[PDB]
Image: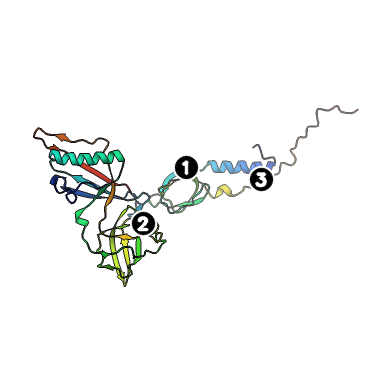
Amino acid sequence: FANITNYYTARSYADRELKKSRYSRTLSFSVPYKFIGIEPNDPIAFTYERYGWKDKFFLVDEVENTRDGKINLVLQEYGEDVFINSEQVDNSGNDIPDISNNVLPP
Amino acid sequence: MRLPDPYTNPEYPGLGFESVNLVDNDPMIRDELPNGKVKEVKISAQYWGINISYPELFPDEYAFLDSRLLEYKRTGDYLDVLLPQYEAFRVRGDTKSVTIPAGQKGSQIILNTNGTLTGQPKAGDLFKLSTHPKVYKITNFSSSGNVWNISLYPDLFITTTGSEKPVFNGILFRTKLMNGDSFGSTLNNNGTYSGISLSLRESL
């Protein structure tokens, strides 16, 4: 992490990434001109009865708009647990100041 | 410029249209969803396609027809094509005292005949405005007094400015000759020209 300096925030973000890595499954399909307005990172519930899917959570990853009113989509599977935060402990006592690089007085 | 037909030129009976083909060209994007609902999308314009076939042509008939076609290709004019089957005279009178309210951009013309026109147009006839060259077919007609409600197949290619005048008789297709890139006619040993076909397209 380049832009994160808070230890607990970085730990939470790493936990989120680890949770998000467990859902690696993408889906692509096309929809008619209706449903216009879909944008990436939008919540979509997929329901395909042939599979064991009933309102499965997905996030838009790729959206392509054509001039003949057809929208191509690529969904990315997510979960609810991705956005809940697990309890952590305090690293307050593990700080290591650099008190070196100077001459100690007598 | 008018295409030679046995109306203006009866001395060349071989110039008659042995068979015409009025082609309805309205390109659309048709998509069939798996739920059984077929959906269409229309963007491009509709243009009447006319295909003319000819019989064996004697040297004088072919000379006249070829001179006219070469004059067309020289001046870059527009061939006018007259279909006899669409020349039934129903509406008669003056089309200058009739008024068309402006702002009509849909697929329907509402005009006040002002009682100056006798007869009524029939569905399936040919209708055209005086300020635009596009040719329309009347799909429905309801008359309530002097105001007429004419319904046209192609959506109005122009927005009425209030100065347009309806034209019911003497309607010509402002066509442009296709397949003119490779245009030819074989002359047989018996002196008659064969294999002449005109694929025309309405270039409004």
Residue extending farthest right: A106
Check disc 3: other Cα within 10 Å, few if <14, some if 14-19, many if 20+. Answer: few
For label 3, the SS is loop
Q: Where, by quadrant of the figure, is residue B89 drawn?
A: bottom left
Q: Where, by quadrant of the figure, is residue B171 drawn?
A: bottom left
Residue under the point 26% across and 52% down: B172
Check disc 2: other Cα within 10 Å, few if <14, some if 14-19, many if 20+. Answer: some
Amino acid type at circle 1 is Arg
Mark 1, residue position: A25
**Label tally:** 3
Locate residue A39 relative to residue A48 in the image: left or right: right
Q: Are marks 3 and 1 on the same chain?
A: yes
**Mark-to-mark CA distance, 3 and 1:** 29 Å
Q: Are marks 3 and 2 on the same chain?
A: no
Mark 3, residue position: A88
For label 2, the SS is loop
- Protein image colouring: rainbow
| Residue B203 is at least partly visible in this image | yes
Q: Where, by quadrant of the figure, is residue B121 drawn?
A: bottom left
Work out whether residue A47 or residue B121 is closer to the camera in this orientation and state it. B121
**Mark-to-mark CA distance, 3 and 2:** 70 Å
**Mark-to-mark CA distance, 1 and 2:** 51 Å
Place of residue B152 in the rendered image (x, y in percent of width and height, measured from the top left): 31, 59
Check residue B156 in the rendering and tell me which mark sits there, or answer none.
Answer: 2
